[PDB]
Length: 316
Length: 313
Ligand SMILES: NC(=O)c1ccc[n+]([C@@H]2O[C@H](COP(=O)([O-])OP(=O)(O)OC[C@H]3O[C@@H](n4cnc5c(N)ncnc54)[C@H](OP(=O)(O)O)[C@@H]3O)[C@@H](O)[C@H]2O)c1
Ligand SMILES: NC(=O)c1ccc[n+]([C@@H]2O[C@H](COP(=O)([O-])OP(=O)(O)OC[C@H]3O[C@@H](n4cnc5c(N)ncnc54)[C@H](OP(=O)(O)O)[C@@H]3O)[C@@H](O)[C@H]2O)c1
Image (cartoon, rainbow over all chains, first blue to last red; front, side, top):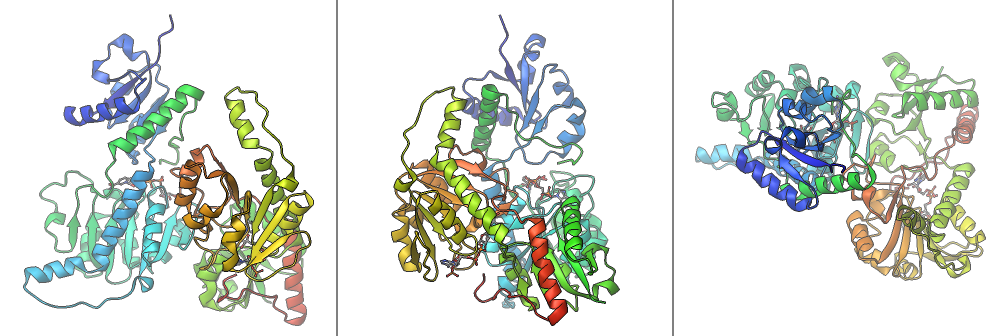
């Protein structure tokens, strides 16, 4: 008798949302024994080699003594790094072509919202004002993308194909057809000097927290507009409000915030130059994500291969 | 006291390696990394030696005269630096031609000698010999008959393959069937069992190998892309691999490099991913070529032949 391995589903989602996930995972991984952490006895916990996680309680993972690796269901991993790094087990984030497709679409959709003056036209409508605003071509309009990763590079390609003059920024050098790529801290402020619409798709780390502070925001040309699809703490909220109120930044589309759901007292809900979205730019698709987890687990069972994991020292 | 700026986004170790080779080939010249020059020293630069430079750095060399790339491919230089109107000199090097012609034959053999099928059998613990047919019975097509493409067609010819080549204007290559013009591409592709791409990326070659052109290849044809990623429609390629119409693809070049982790190419059973290594620039030979060009400029004022921006390659 040699106990076979099992999988713990470890989340702090609602019971309904966790059940939805369970069904999708069970269908994608039909040969596997997958159970909610709370359903396992102490002896069953010792049989777990893989945890599938969604905002897991880190104390639960510490009670899986033979855990080998961890699969998250989200692209962002800053809290996993902070809370689970000490267990020294590989953390596999979600990398999914469908997530990339969806985010790249979002990036273009909300770049268009800003570019085509949709907020100004909405304000005019409320005022019963009929007034056409001047148009300038995308080829004359510089769009900057911060982050050229699974999501950021995909976004730069959609924005390129829409005809924008696209500049991208990342930590290490990239080559992206039809996109001007910049790398390193040393080139950021120069890049920003040129950017009329700025899209943020960075991960949150010690190095990106507060990147878009008063100084960096002041690098943007007058009337520049910003889209934050990354994490709230990358963009200094106080500095953003000052820049909006001084007329130096024209508008901000914010999908991510320090506290979610955004508290009712936030000035962002009522600011005339802010568009609030409830963290929906690129929602995980449970079908495609489950099939990816499924393939990763199958490959592990077949060959011992653990998928690419987060470098803790890098932080993403 | 003119000086030379070395402008790259290579690693510090690779750029230092290059700097040593250039310093040896150009002993009388003051060559420094762009990041080491003060604003005043930047004003003394008349020549930039470049390898994936940030274009904004070149825009800060106000008395720049001309630019020498260390790479054969120039499409980003054209797009990003064309506006400065300084001559762009691409790398043409017999050793680069030799290396790429070698790569073309090496990876043609990888396909021809069934190396992927044998690797799949090995993973399955299956012992099974596959039928062999002579190279003289296998048609190989080369897209691009330039510095690299013609050299590749000659190596393939000499290995005994039945070689067809395609370019914009007519060529005569002994022992090779040469086709020219858009009008002859689809007819050529109809005959090709292994297709090697050695075109430059331009407005005219982007998306050349789309669903329609890929459908011209005979069933089971195999492809080698050593040109640029955008020349080959990725979605169309995957559909052709999955339908069984294309047998295998060796891909060295992609629209985004490094290839994103989400790319279907990494995991596809009928795809071999190479990290843009088919023909790396040889720092010794390329340095001696840059050296001779700079020396001739210092001696006579001659700027070497440069890229025609309207032509795009
Ligand atoms: N709002 C939503 O609905 C939503 C949904 C999903 C994800 N997200 C967010 O999107 C982020 C990106 O996801 P992803 O999968 O694209 O991540 P990823 O593949 O790791 O890419 C991250 C990119 O950011 C760059 N970067 C990181 N630190 C940097 C620094 N200090 N300086 C300059 N560039 C730096 C990286 O540079 P290198 O390439 O050189 O490593 C890389 O290009 C997530 O972390 C998450 O916060 C939001
Ligand atoms: N993967 C790697 O490591 C690597 C390394 C080096 C180079 N490369 C790639 O290899 C490419 C070729 O280099 P090269 O030195 O051979 O260039 P080249 O000497 O300029 O030759 C280019 C060839 O392509 C043909 N061509 C260009 N546009 C065409 C079109 N629209 N239709 C048909 N034929 C067309 C040219 O026709 P004509 O003869 O009529 O002018 C010529 O035969 C580079 O641009 C680079 O992208 C890749």
